[PDB]
Image 1 (cartoon, rainbow, N blue to C red):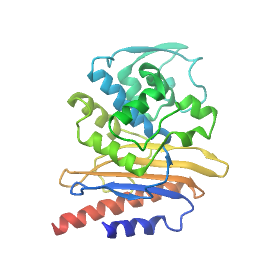
Image 2: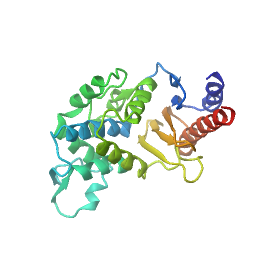
Image 3: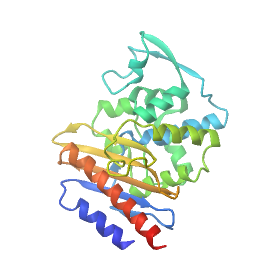
Length: 278
């Protein structure tokens, strides 16, 4: 739809950032893409793809949700966002895969993320999995530790807005995971504690939203990435897929999140307009 595209452009024009958007409503044949040729750093958004690969290996019986990993407090990535390190006491403890997944997805935990990467063969294994789903415009080459070591690396874990739309559609179609794995991932994405003022920012109270955020620190005067992508359930229970990636922004943190909230609200209102007519 040209009208929705124009409404979204009216939000991003004038903001000192480059914004990518993908909107796919339930009656749309193709998704609406804003800035389709730009490469967007994913930051923690790729923990979504990683959870799908891990659950896919659980579905195949290659991994078990209760399989546990020994965590040595001295050997994991130090001084990074890792809530799991505060959930257990001791210099050494063991955590099941089920909980590492929950912490990576819902809490965007960086240590849980890298521990999961180690069970499946690293970034290379995730990249193969993504390509195997037919998504060519998403690249994964580094884990959190490597992204932590060199701040240019984050740009190498990128996605196009078509790639963001496809991962949401694959997930939404419930064709990649067993019913159990699908229900677990939906649970962790609805329970996310991060980014409450992004996609969910201006939606009505009670709207169900399964989403995953991605954020970088302010370095060299800009925020490389402020992202949120997810599934919004409409009043009739049908899904609305929305992904918003704000790249290389020189705006305040508050403004970066408001761009995402406004785009989500505009897409949501547009779907109500269609339900209103049809």
